[PDB]
Length: 363
Image (cartoon, rainbow, N blue to C red; front, side, top):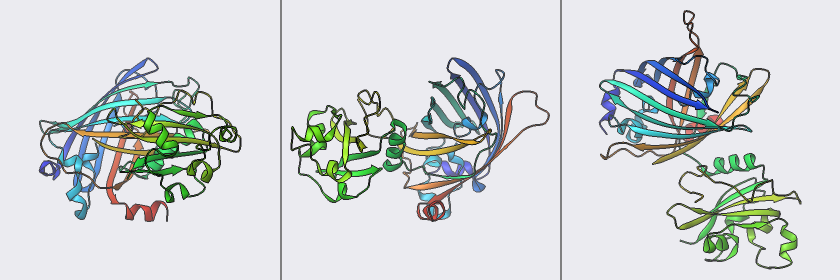
């Protein structure tokens, strides 16, 4: 609305981070300027508790999208600037592939005439030898195009690759029940065919609000002709787990995790958490998800899966966003005259329509 006028000039940034990773606590303080008309951030961050227990590039995403430069046609959808000055809360989960996770809560708001990002972070389940605690990541950050609109397919890709399944799909109402999204699919017939209410695997799990587990699909087909759901036959599932999805403490949909070719359910599939991986839909605000590639110094790429929630702080009206991208240019630098573990950051963040972004990333 009118929080945009606060960003016409140069704006001072102040950043505070409170962190605790596997019990190792640390603090980071940040200082600099932001030019929103150019999407520009100039910042210096210092670890004021000693050595940073984790690598600097893993905290960049955590360390103010209200400074993105939105092209003229898109300004009408600038949510972050519209939540200003009252602010917004950024809650985030970052899963480091085959390693632990960050959970972060951040208040972003104007303090006087300075934009302040105040962050609290708890990281758990990290490997002592692992890429993170081992400090095996290259000090840089790939210039990237990033989502900032969620996308259930990328969430399903994450879940599939993480629980090491071959197939995943989500059933939602359209109000009957369609299999809307799927990852690892080999056909699209799961969407082309829709069952009447209560019918099928999704119908069962929604009606009963309880998981169904099939260790071997063929043998159970010998008991119940039902289990021959269109999804099961279309994707040739030999084992599967079907989970109920909530969000209103009322059963709303279904998550299907499937295996192929007599390969068995990975260990502990029985006890699986959708936790915060599906935005609105739970296990039992503006959501987004994306993925970050951290170069490993001794050759490699460490993945960081990001799940995002942004809620305005005030009660006044805020602009709502459409589906868009963020083109981010990052430069990681060091202050030659700084004895403390630190980071110099120069950044440019530009908003992009889904077209001008698909065309670059995938075409």
